[PDB]
Amino acid sequence: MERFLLNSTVLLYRLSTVSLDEVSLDERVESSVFLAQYEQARSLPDHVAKSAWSYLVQQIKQRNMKLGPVAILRLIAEKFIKNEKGGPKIDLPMFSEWQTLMSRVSCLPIIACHQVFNPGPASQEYSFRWPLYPYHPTVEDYITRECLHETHQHLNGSTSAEECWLDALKHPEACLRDFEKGWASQEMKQLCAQIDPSLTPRIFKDRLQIACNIREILCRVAQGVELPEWIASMQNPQQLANSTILHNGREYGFATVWPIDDKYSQESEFCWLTGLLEKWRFNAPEGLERLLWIYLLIQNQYLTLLVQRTMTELREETEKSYLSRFKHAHGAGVYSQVRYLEGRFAPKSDPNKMQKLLFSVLRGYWEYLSAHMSMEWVHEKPLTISQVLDNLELVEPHGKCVELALVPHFIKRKPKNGEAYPHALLFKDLKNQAAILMDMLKSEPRLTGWIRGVDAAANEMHAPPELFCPLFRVLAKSGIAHFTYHVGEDFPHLISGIRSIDDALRFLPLRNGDRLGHCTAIGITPSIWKRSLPLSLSMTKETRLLDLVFIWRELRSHPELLRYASDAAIEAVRLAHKVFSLEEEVSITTLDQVFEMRGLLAESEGLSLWLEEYERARELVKTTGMKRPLKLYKQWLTSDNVRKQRAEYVEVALEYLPDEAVVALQQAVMAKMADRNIAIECPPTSQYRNVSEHHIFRWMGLPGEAIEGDVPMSICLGSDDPGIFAADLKSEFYHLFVVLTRKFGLSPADALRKVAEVNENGRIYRFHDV
Amino acid sequence: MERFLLNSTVLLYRLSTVSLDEVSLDERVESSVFLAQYEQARSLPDHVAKSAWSYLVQQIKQRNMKLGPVAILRLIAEKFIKNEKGGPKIDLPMFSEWQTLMSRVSCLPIIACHQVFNPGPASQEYSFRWPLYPYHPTVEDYITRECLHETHQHLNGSTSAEECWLDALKHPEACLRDFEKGWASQEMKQLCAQIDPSLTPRIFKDRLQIACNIREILCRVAQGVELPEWIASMQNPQQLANSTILHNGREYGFATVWPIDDKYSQESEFCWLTGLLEKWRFNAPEGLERLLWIYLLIQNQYLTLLVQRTMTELREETEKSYLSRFKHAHGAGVYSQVRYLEGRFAPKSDPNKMQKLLFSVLRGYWEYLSAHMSMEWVHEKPLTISQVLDNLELVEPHGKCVELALVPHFIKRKPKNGEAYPHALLFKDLKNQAAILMDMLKSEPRLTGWIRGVDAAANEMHAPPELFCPLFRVLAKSGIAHFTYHVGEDFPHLISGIRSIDDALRFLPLRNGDRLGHCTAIGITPSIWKRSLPLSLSMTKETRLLDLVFIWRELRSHPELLRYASDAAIEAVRLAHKVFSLEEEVSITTLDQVFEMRGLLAESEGLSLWLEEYERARELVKTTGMKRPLKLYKQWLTSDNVRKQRAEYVEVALEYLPDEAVVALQQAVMAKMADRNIAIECPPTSQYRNVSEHHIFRWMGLPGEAIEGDVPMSICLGSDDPGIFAADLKSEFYHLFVVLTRKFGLSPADALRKVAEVNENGRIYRFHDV
Amino acid sequence: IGITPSIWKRSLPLSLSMTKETRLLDLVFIWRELRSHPELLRYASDAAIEAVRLAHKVFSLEEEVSITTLDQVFEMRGLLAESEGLSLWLEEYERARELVKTTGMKRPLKLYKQWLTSDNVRKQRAEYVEVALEYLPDEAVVALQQAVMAKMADRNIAIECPPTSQYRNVSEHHIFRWMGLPGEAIEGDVPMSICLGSDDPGIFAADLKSEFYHLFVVLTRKFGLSPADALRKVAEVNENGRIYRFHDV
Ligand SMILES: [Zn+2]
Ligand SMILES: [Zn+2]
């Protein structure tokens, strides 16, 4: 429960609102804790909270200390972090729980408290490194031998959330600008209201600047410098909502001097916090400790809102952040811990911005390499992308350092109210971006060795994959090997997700060894897919009809489900009749022929490198006996009536199909996949009670999770956990190892090689040049 | 999904605040629904809600309604309720969803709308009856042939919460007094914040008066009488927060003539709502539907508060509520659906109030019996308890009507800061009440024929059973037959609840055929008992030590857990040494002999009907070798440091014992159950996702639910669901029936019998006189 | 749903003549059932084909009609003729309004009207066609039959059984096969809530008590059940009489 006292919206209000000399807020802190649990962990049975709080307070009073940041952090550090071998580490049994706490709290304060109150041997000068980790010699030797391989880094640009808070403190105005530009959006209305009811942009700025001011003041006291006299005027936290304080007539600026150049550096934060805590080892002023309360609380609230969520992204268009990611990916040892890194990046609409971003990333990689290996760099200070390449070709794949592969994102937005065919404007945008990419490759053909493969991300329902097939094929002929597309992550229905996955398979120009993405649909079981959700699910008519045709096709060969297959046939015919407003009798067969054309470009022939696909409809139209498919698909694309019908909603009864049938669909899907030799990135991520049910294990063949009709699926790794701070690929590696060893009782060797197949598959299906 | 539109606190806030002429609040209601769903059902993944509301609005626009309570109740009634055989009945597969809905909403409006818009045959004049039930010929034939058994009804006095609402409107000031006296105590503050952050007694009175005024105004429209003028002045809902409205200098009242004398009756509500809906069949004024909306909301929210929760009970001290209870318990047939009723009521500490309550209950019962049967009644208008007994002495156990059994409660409060021994003052209050009880019994020996047994209710941790043993023995000698004690309901640890149950067995004077209560500790499995609980659970030191003693005692003979038993012994020795401040060596044997003395009365010898348990310690003191036992027990009861360290808080691992070992302790307890012929009352109720997980099934032996060593133990039924409105014993009967037949596929006969053995256990262990 | 095919063809001619509608609906039903059983899909396909042919005759159809469409035709046999295609009566007068709105039902509705009205169609309905006595196997019969008892249990509908042509002896009585008697019950059977009826066509002075005795004696002697066994079995149906009594409660 401790992480309440560090992450609490109501406590944040109360502490920020009460005066600094109030004292004796124990009851209200406790009540705020109970409200926080009621909001967050509703399931706790109303008495565990009171008991655990009686404890927490009891331990505090035993240790003769005050309810404080230092108190809670001390308890947490003592409970979790141990110093072993090298640096602080996380106990193997407690690692998962520590991750759960990470899902709510920042670890820098905890780490500083650990160092100050129980430092390890005074022989290894420790430098801050996030996140903290457990130790297993087998795992360590394995990583030393083979290193790790990143393929899914797209959660928040390419960095952890923690440094973004410091970036905010560095450009508070930029973050307010982004906050506001988006405050006009609907979705974030609900996001912000549900995280913090009365969040609002003015209070956004107020909390940000208050945090800046508290950091400054606490830094002054940590350095132990004179407690400036306007502190006396400082009485109410709301005073920290302004850039200057008024003591008597004068407006005093809080700005001050810090030893380090990068005043917003994580290292600066850490040194500051260590100094403060060591000053505060025996006792603390109440005003300042409450200040640190609100400081940590605002940190955490900001970090959540960010994680549960373009210009705060643009500011990362320098060769500083990329160097940072690269240095972090490289360990503290001479050899980098990750062997092969996939660098995923959002394309822009302007050639200037793409060339800027590309030069930034390329240069940063060059400096990362130069900082580790010495040689004649030709252009010692490269200024152009061509110069950077000139520098880079000289590198050989020894493996001392990481190997970079660059993948642009394809962001799928919702269709708009008015357009010739669905997603037409989005298609135009993507065509613009892709053409620019192609032209940059034209200009610098050597870029084919660094820009390898394109991913298709953002919310799936906003666009079906068939929209991207012409894009992917044109890019391929441009020289883009390898492709990726997010499938199966979220869906109106599990059958819908499975159908979407097969659509991608059968339509996308995916070759041997390509990689799809989460594909959670074919991993999640129908036992654990419906546990708190309504018995029926409303969804779009188009989605329903496509899924019904999918059920048809997949179950046509299954003797045990032919009843369901006939039902799918009948109901798909009826839905087609309604959506297309049909009066003639239309066969499931011709529906199927219509639906197999979904990969065709809208504007091909029914509506340089684009000529092939522009004519791709020509041989189809040449096929005489496909009249009805042509006209029906043209109606599907253009007809206003058909489009409104497609948008229409209607229920699916949950138990439309037996879970056995769902599993059969899944298994047909894995069969087709494995036939085509495609891999599945699986990052650890809503409905799972604990990680133990993660479908990764079913894909991994664990007894008690795997199903009889199952296959291997070439799972690969990816460091993208939506609801955590300061996560890493090796963090996920350790997560999987510990869960295997503990919950499944596998011996350390067993867990090691279990995870190792997925890791080495990461290398195997790397897109990087060979 | 619809639950959120009919109960939403934040929705209530803003709709009540906005002007009645605001209009076009669709997006507003959307935000309200998303917030309410987030706060209540957190698990739903953020998009199913969007789809569900999309289809809701699709329905509303297609069928051409306005987003409003009318359309909502219409969709509900269509989706749930139907006319079959006699009156409306709930579709069987939908009963679980409907009772879930009743967990948050009331059915009066829904049933009104159903009757209004799809009435059955216009020949069975439809007198409202609550709640609404399903139809199964086997079920109805069984209830007719046999009839049912109420054994456990202590939730809201003995009434369903919905009637408490019209009670509040009858005496709103009384509800205000009850609210405020209690609003000063913390736990209600935590609750008020958790349910309604800004609840307060102020807005409490405000919302109550608003509700009454809405009732009046919409009565004006329903009777279709002239739409009085001050409606024009009425522009904001808050204007309804006052008893009068100021139009132009004049303050106009809200009250009127209503057709029925009892203006606060559920039947009045029903006929009224029917009239309102009939009038509003095709359309209605926007502001008026909004007023109805707010009425319904407030209705739901305060009903929620009430259920989850003195003078509101005191006002129920007339022979009216109890007559109503009896009539409700009896169906609409000549024969009563229940045969045997158990009437549980609090024993008051004033003899006058106690005899008042008792004459009230007796007179209500007699009048009911008169209302259904004819003979000479002797005192046609009885006045005294003696007179009503004279009347009732002529009644015979034919079975036409209900047979009542009266049980005083014992509400056990937390121990206070200062007292000679723990819970001493509570013991004194109970002794006062029991003295009063035996006084009235002495005065009227006949009362033994209606007061059959006493129950120990209230929060378990507030007091342990052993202190009641002298009380129960004294009462038994006075002439009270059968006893009850709530066990297993709430606990800090599962083993601790198990130990509590054993202690009750081995200390309370329980006899053959007695009953305990919920005993959920013994039904909940270790597997599904730890789903969101912290990896470590936290207890009082005294509880921890007693559990250690229990574990070792019970596992002494288990060869497979001897390790665990030996541990428990060791840590028990350690804890006893620290607690008793023991310098010498205390054997776990000695601790056994100490803790077996717990049933001893505190003020007997180590500190007429009472003389026996005053001298009971004489035999033990005569016992020579028990020196050390007695002195340690005295230390335990009295030593201030000892009571302090008892109150202090010690932690224990969640997985302190293996799941199997916990079940083994459970099985020792099941064996004791069967051996002593003690029944267990199992009503339907926090950790269960769906009702199918209910431990009731574990006892009923459902394959895959019964554990290997399971033992039948005379489970009995109880109509007490903490989180539902207008619950009934027959209702939960249907619930169990449907659950068996569907989630386990059992045939109607199988489910009928499987519930029937429990029902008939009810008969077998009636407390009623023979 | 009682008589087993084994004892259904004991003196029957090897072919049976019946009306064309009966034949067509039979084929349609056979398909509707046998779509799902892996062991009878051949028969289901045969029925679909032949039903298509027979409908092409009965409707004199010139276009092509799918068995799905035939089903959509014959699913609407519950519609009132003069509802919309030919106070309390209102609701069923207008019920066809929703369907006629249904756009995809064009061909079904027109076919239904043809069937109800067309004189040529009605003449063809009255026409007769032969069917082989073993048109389908006993196993197929019993599969259909067990599906029927499945829906029986699903809808909680009872069967009102009196005692009565082909049966040589009362021991051959179908009542027993419902009653689950070993050697009389069939594997894929389900319980179906039988109730009694005192209606014997070919006797005088017969009563429910008389039938009770008859059943008890036959159970006891021909099947050797103990008195308790036979009494319990007979009761089952007897008190099922209570259970599904129409009498008001
Ligand atoms: Zn992804
Ligand atoms: Zn209870």
Image (cartoon, coloured by chain):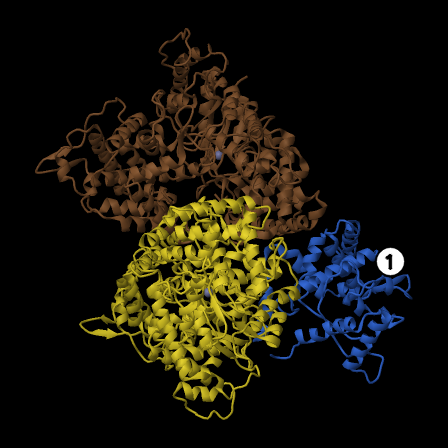
Chain colours: A brown, B yellow, C blue
Seen at 31% across and 49% down, the residue is A30
Residue C233: name its quadrant: bottom right
- Which residue lies under the disc numbered 1? C134
Would you place residue B725 above or below residue A614 in this image?
below
Would you place residue A102 above or below residue B593 in this image?
above
Q: Front-most of B747 and C244?
A: B747
Side of C86 relative to A128 (left or right): right
Give the x, y percent position of residue C91.
57, 70
Point out the image quarter for the C terminus of chain B. bottom right
* Type of amino acid at the residue the image marks with label 1: Glu
Give the x, y percent position of residue C209.
77, 81
Residue B127 showing in the rendered view: no
Would you place residue B231 above or below residue A509 in this image?
below
Give the x, y percent position of residue B107.
46, 67
Q: Front-most of A480 and B15?
A: B15
Residue A460 showing in the rendered view: yes
- Parent chain of label 1: C
Side of C194 relative to A311 (left or right): right
For mark 1, does the 10 Å Cα neighbourhood hold few (<14), some (14 to 19), or many (20 or more) residues? few
Side of B422 relative to B765 (left or right): left
